[PDB]
Image: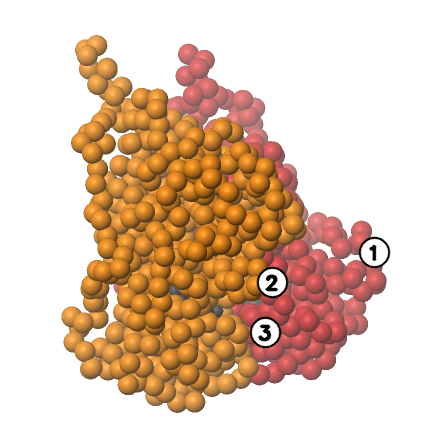
Chain colours: A orange, B red
Amino acid sequence: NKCDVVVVGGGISGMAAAKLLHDSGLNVVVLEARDRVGGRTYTLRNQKVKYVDLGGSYVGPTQNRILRLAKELGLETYKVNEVERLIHHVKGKSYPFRGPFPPVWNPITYLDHNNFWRTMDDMGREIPSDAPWKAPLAEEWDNMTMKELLDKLCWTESAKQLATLFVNLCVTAETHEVSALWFLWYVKQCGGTTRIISTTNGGQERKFVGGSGQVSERIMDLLGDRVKLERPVIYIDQTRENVLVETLNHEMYEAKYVISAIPPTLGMKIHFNPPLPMMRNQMITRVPLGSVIKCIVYYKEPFWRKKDYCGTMIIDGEEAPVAYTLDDTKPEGNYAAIMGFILAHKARKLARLTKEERLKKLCELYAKVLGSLEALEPVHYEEKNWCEEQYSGGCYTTYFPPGILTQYGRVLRQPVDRIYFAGTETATHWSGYMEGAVEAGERAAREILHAMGKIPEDEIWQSEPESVDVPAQPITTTFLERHLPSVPGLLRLIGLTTI
Amino acid sequence: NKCDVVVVGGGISGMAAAKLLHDSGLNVVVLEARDRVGGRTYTLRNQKVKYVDLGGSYVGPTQNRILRLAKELGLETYKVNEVERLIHHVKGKSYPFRGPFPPVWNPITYLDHNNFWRTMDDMGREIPSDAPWKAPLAEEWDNMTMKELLDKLCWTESAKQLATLFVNLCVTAETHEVSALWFLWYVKQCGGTTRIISTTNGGQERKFVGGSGQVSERIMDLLGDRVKLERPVIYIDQTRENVLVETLNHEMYEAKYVISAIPPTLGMKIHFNPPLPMMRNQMITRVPLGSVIKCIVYYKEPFWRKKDYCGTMIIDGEEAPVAYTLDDTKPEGNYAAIMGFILAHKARKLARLTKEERLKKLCELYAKVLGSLEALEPVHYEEKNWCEEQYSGGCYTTYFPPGILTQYGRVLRQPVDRIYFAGTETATHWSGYMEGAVEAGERAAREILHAMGKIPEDEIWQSEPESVDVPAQPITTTFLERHLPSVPGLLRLI
Ligand SMILES: *[C]C1=C([C])[C]=[C@@]23C(=[C]1)N([C][C]([O])[C]([O])[C]([O])[C]OP([O])(=O)OP([O])(=O)O[C][C]1O[C](N4[C]=NC5=C4N=[C]N=C5[N])[C]([O])[C]1[O])C1=NC(=O)[N]C(=O)C1=N2/C3=[C]\[C]=[N+](/[C])[C]1[C][C]C2=C1[C]=C([O])[C]=[C]2
Ligand SMILES: *Cc1cc2c(cc1C)nc1c(=O)[nH]c(=O)nc-1n2C[C@H](O)[C@H](O)[C@H](O)COP(=O)(O)OP(=O)(O)OC[C@H]1O[C@@H](n2cnc3c(N)ncnc32)[C@H](O)[C@@H]1O
């Protein structure tokens, strides 16, 4: 009934927030709408898979908060398989390679690819992580979709097709759906194109032994019966002395403060008294989540390793159900599996099919890409379509359509009286990830602690020690990469030796 | 407790739907979240204004359904003032004119303007009203914003500025915010550029004597205590034999069917069991409403008419708080007033000011455009910012960002088991208006009537007799307008 802080939502952010508050001796209640904690992380367990992450899963270098927190909860990581060759499948052929970036031979194409990625990071450098609307050209970059930007920047179809896959993969949305400013912010705040795309030394280096769902499950264990499941919040009243929070089943909770730790658009499921301020009122109708089906096909053995393939497939073009895969085999080498994402419009389109129909399409795709009939012989299949989740709205995260981030960005984490905002969307380093979930949860908790006089303002935002288990190598660029001209820069140079 | 149909929302669409069902002998309950009916229409009454429409207001030729319905409720229209000259204010100077289109004098510019509007209507011709996503170039047109389209089409800055003002005014959103396909559909479904922009012979011809709020009020009057106010729906359960609808104050309603007659995105304020299908689930997080403050400044007299101005100002450029105005004086010639809209990003920006600060900016603006010190002497001011409305989400209506209408358009009025969808957003003629609200409410009601076996399939969509009080003259184009080349068409000819 009465406590210090009600935390709305028990995903990683809500739980990290509750934990920090509880570790400070405050009385917290977590109101979780679902019959489970974890939210957009969700580890399934059964005999066939032992365990499998059907939601968020990968962690890696620079993601120190999720790594620290999981470690304290007694969790361990292992390295995603990347020993053997990666594959880029383009125009129906596979080209095996090594290193994070699919290589390119043609010198003109090479110059355009190089400049594309370089320019993403160049542009990124002008974008404050904590205030992207302050970039010098914020409006100009916000009033254009990623599709316009790629049209402008890519002088080859090849660079454009790969850049498109990259956007689709990073943010489970189409290039024409999303703002260029927001997309560029998003990548920059993960440390740039290399850090974000890499398995070794990047965001996909590792997974947790046993599944990421353990993070929220273990904090639930620690909080005992402070975590209330099947308590969807429907109503928040801030007109009186104490904040009142009512759940759908009719329970009523009183607190000094509230943490909203749910996706920004899911705030729409709460009726507010007094009404939200105008800007948040509209903000929450303007920030949708992406579309993805996570798909895991199981095999007797990891046969691809025998062909010197690690299981990483970068798959170009419209006909492919899945554009990207990673080896999902257990660290002991059993429950051999290929993980793949069905992205954006493909999530929407292929959802009309049955589970067995999608499994067939993936197997046939993988058999072609790996050149292996063994791909046609799955032993099991698990998949989750996150578009269908009432209390997620999609996955991995919230994207910003053109014009929104400069108009409404400021509002995202601005307190509304005694409501403070956690949730990975409000993070400034790896927002969209489990990492940002922890950052934003602990920052919101601390904001409340500051409101209560327990900590000074300087302690709201707090840095994090580098994980000793997963250290970060720095990101390096060669001299040519840095200085080779772009395609139009080459044209202008050829033009100059004619005049 | 138990009835035949729960109608969620008491705005024009909800009320039209409830009325039709009641007139058929069914038992309806309207659950309205606010302490009043009307929704995006809202007539304020006080001594100073007598009455004033602070939400939806204008009606005109071809809007036969709202006209028929209002007439039946005993309501009358009068003509918006357009006797004297209109003003176009461009680069800080007023150029008075007659007719609906501001004239353009430079030859090259004239060609570019002409082609821009013409091309809007040409493009619209390939867009089915009931299925815009079936336009032959739907994906191409949907994956680009109106800003890209204008950049492509407008060879002059003047045509581009005016076309931008046009979009901002039509849909209370920025050209870079909205899909080209959706916006082109939107205009086409109101009958094209001329019909949609015109006062005489178009959407802005008329207002209702006493306020448009009376439409919903008078229906609520007819339904008595069937209309429940301050009943925000929070929950809809379709797992059992009858549909269960719970309101925030804890009441529970049972019905055979439900009509959702609220803005598509406001569906998010309802928890559903079972969950909505995947497509609707994500659809409702992708369809925001625009941004507008409606602002009405009152004067002792309609002084503008003395200078042979009617009160219509078309005002170009960033610095102007308001891009468009209309005379809001009562038909009797008193409560003289000028109505203007603060649109899109300007609604966002100027909301930071106080009421009195916005009043000042608006009087100074009107003093410049009208060339009158009299504009600086207002006797009263009413305004409403719809962005702040929890149970609207904005005004006038729902816009579609790039990519959404083709992926999710089909889903808008698709029934979800026993939930049918009204609301102006689901209409196919004057969607976004009071007209489309009636069309959509009456169609949804008839869909339920069909599901019940009372009427055949062919009766779900029903045409409407032309109003005798407000007849439509047809839209005409001259021979030159139809055949003059574009600016690149002229270049290719040279
Ligand atoms: C706001 C506005 C303004 C300011 C203006 C205007 C408008 C608006 N409009 C629109 C109208 O109004 C609309 O459409 C209608 O109203 C709609 O209806 P419906 O569909 O029915 O809807 P609503 O109303 O919203 O209702 C709903 C209801 O529900 C409820 N809820 C919610 N949620 C809930 C509930 N309940 C229970 N539960 C839950 N949960 C709410 O509350 C409500 O009630 C318009 N229209 C017309 O027609 N007219 C007019 O005038 C209008 N307006 C505008 C206009 C403008 N204009 C025209 C302009 C000028 C010049 C120009 C233009 C445009 C163009 O195009 C060009 C030029
Ligand atoms: C879905 C997904 C996510 C994902 C990804 C792949 C997929 C398919 N891969 C990731 C990865 O490999 N590495 C990574 O770091 N992140 C990855 N992501 C995203 C990641 O899962 C999310 O960023 C993270 O889980 C975010 O967590 P957060 O705590 O910030 O938010 P949430 O998980 O959605 O939790 C919100 C909880 O709130 C509940 N809820 C919703 N509405 C209510 C109401 N009204 N009342 C009470 N509770 C509510 C939800 O049930 C949820 O539990």
Give residue A429's quadrant in the image: bottom left
Classify residue B258 as left or right of residue B324.
right
Q: Which amino acid does label 2 sit on?
A: Leu
Mark-to-mark CA distance, 1 and 3 = 31 Å
The residue located at (44%, 80%) in the rendering is A227
The residue located at (42%, 12%) in the rendering is B494
Q: Residue B235 carries which label?
A: 3
The chain containing the residue under callout 2 comes to B
- Residue under numbered circle 2: B276
The residue located at (50%, 72%) in the rendering is A36
Residue B188 rendering spot, x and y as whole percentages: 58, 41
- Residue under numbered circle 1: B456
Quarter occupied by the N terminus of chain A: bottom left
Quarter occupied by the C terminus of chain A: top left
Instruction: Confirm if mark 2 falls within 8 A of ligand 2.
Output: no
Closer to us: mark 1 or mark 2?
A: 2
Contact, CB < 8 Å: mark 3 with mark 2? no
Contact, CB < 8 Å: mark 1 with mark 2? no
Residue B29 rendering spot, x and y as whole percentages: 67, 75
Residue A184 visible in the snapshot:
no
The residue located at (22%, 64%) in the rendering is A464
The chain containing the residue under callout 1 comes to B
The tag earlier along the polypeptide, 3 or 2, is: 3
Q: In this view, does B118 lie above or below A20?
A: above
| Numbered marks: total | 3
